[PDB]
Length: 257
Image (cartoon, rainbow, N blue to C red; front, side, top):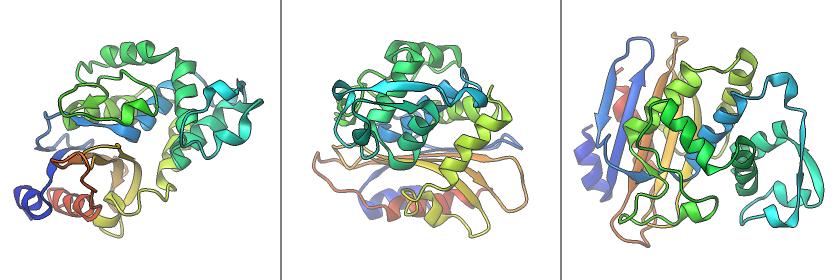
């Protein structure tokens, strides 16, 4: 199935970057075009924090007040005036896509500027974090704010997590959250073969049908992962996205491996 054909069928724009970490073979399609990354950045922020906090120290607590709360914080709203461990913060952001948990994580790292700084060091000059949740969800094709390209985002996910500086315990804790996440069952998880294990983080911005999924894919019989970045959008501001597009893009791309 050709990807050009998939863009016509759904009337959408597809951006893909896949890297087999075993062979180093790559599959690219509009892999240098910018798209809003939305909530898939939650994975990037959790990883960056886990580089500076050992597994044994995730029990450490942070205080949450009224001022921290942003829209769509299903777990964090129950914590106003309370303390929460860093472990529970990462779980709320990854599993429930909690917006307040993500802003607090970025604060712990030091703020948007420390995140950007870390990306530079990893060699990522493209990913451009500017706003916190939920302003980062307001995408305009005329702005570079909070956008990245499928190639830049995928090489960063490979460096941070697959070939990164995480300890065994931290890497496993994070990947297990991503494997047991039920929010991405309609995406990459829906299009790859049944024997394949998929650890993903999905995303949806408010405008232009911005629907994304990023994953670590384990083919039956291979312990090294295939990193898979799928960013898609439509032409009108108010377009509603169709998840089958991403399931189909994933089935089509996996045929190359």
